[PDB]
Length: 177
Length: 83
Length: 63
Length: 63
Image (cartoon, rainbow over all chains, first blue to last red; front, side, top):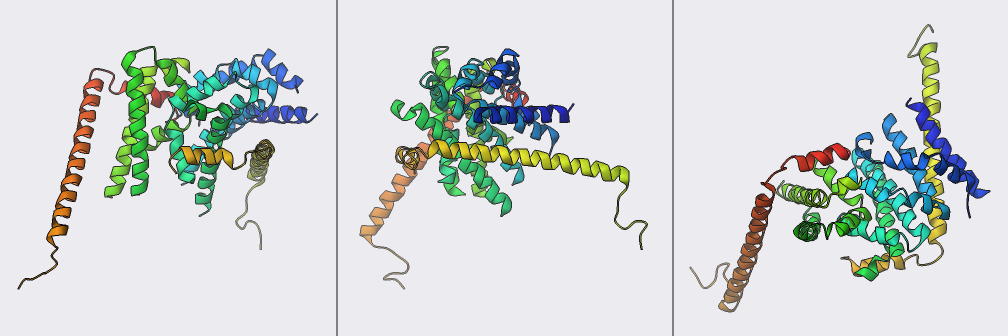
């Protein structure tokens, strides 16, 4: 089904969200035991094929959920062990049509950005490789930011530009030079 | 339109140096290439999708070279196997 | 007047109602997720180094 | 006629000549470097897998 999977995916976001407000959580732990996080990271591959349209809105909730798990300290452990760096590489993902394109890059950048700065110095080694292996692309975004559809497009650039900036200061790429 | 063309010219120059370096020695540098694409993921995706009057043609030409630059590093580094 | 003036039928009326409800639910969920993410980023960035994080890059990278 | 008609002076004439020579040298060097790089890429890519390298990505990434 197309609508059941969408509502179910968005439902999990509310469960984990309200659970944190109640440093750990039993909801996120159960998802790992049920092999949900495993299959979820596997579906990240070939995301370009999936991405108003029903398939587009479905992917939004998918990446949105992963972003929430990377905010808690315990999520970095289970999420990092899923080897998400190699999953987003096989897909080769890295006026209104362009706005949707940046929306996908922002969603992925936030998941990776929050994940590295979640655990600590155990994930910085991977962040440096992502910026070095994909260098240049981020440079174009950080320099671009430096009528309705136009403002919406520029807004995504600001979020996208600030997304990588958080990973840089959090990963310590300046020290590598 | 001319200012943007110069911006991509710099990214292409850097991408070519890194792209040719990884595919030069062999499997000793692929470990670094994967980190560069994973740490800077998303940015390259925008370029590879863009390509897929005088100043306009010049700007688009850099996009083709920039898009093809990273593509060479992917196939040479083997990022598809990592998924 | 009556008997139809830019109107619809009940079979289509209920379908349009359901579609509108679904679209509104999806929009509300997206907006709430965006607001929660923005609040989280504001709470995590308001600690310290608000402008230095970008100044270091503006000084390192080409302005 | 004569004695000046949209003309220049020798002190500026030699400077303009030198500037033109320098600009032409820089342009020729840039063009030769670009041509050498293009030839190198053509020689390295003409071996095999001309269209597969992009087809794999078009199939993996969003078209």
